[PDB]
Length: 296
Image (cartoon, rainbow, N blue to C red):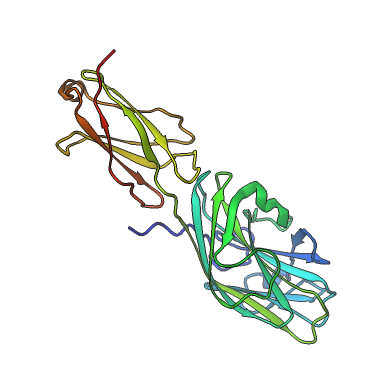
């Protein structure tokens, strides 16, 4: 089934509103970005909102899109960046960001990064290089990161979280020479889903008359936090004995407690079945099997 969309984009510059987006600029297009102020009286107004008093860049947000405009008054190199926040993510889970790269004016180059969530203050700041604190194995499908004149269209970004909690999609653009006219860049239809593969059963231990079933989990893609993995244990006749959900960084072995009747019903060398469902990504493993052994 359909995994939940974890993007928190409500299309507003109102700093305290739910799902508001971060707005920043980098004088000289460096690693460091500071907040992009706009006139206080116009913060909820639709259309192009000027960089307060300086008016070198204008910004525009709505329910579907986020956009930047570079004016002739810009001192080049100069960069505007946006932060599109996510809902709380799980540590060591795999995610898939999708969005559409809209118009890119001639002279504008674009980069896509993962970052900390916009902290909902006019004092917020960030560094591009902060990416390595939040995400690993970041990959734009069929493209490299860094400022480039990208093709317009559907974009896919996959990554693994190094932390728990909200993060952001960082939409960066810049100009390297003084604009000769209004230069617009737009991003739209922003989504993020969990794509974590469920764990695999490495080994299972069960004994006749013993209520404690010990399951050892493994992973083929280097995942160590099995949090959210729904483990179902069945007897050889296909009857469900018990279901457990793995907690945050729960270490091996994962314990399953049977009832006294279930423990007595086990037979020596019986083949038990294990099915694992990743709760967030909705992906389900292949069937795994192990034998009920002899109680030492």
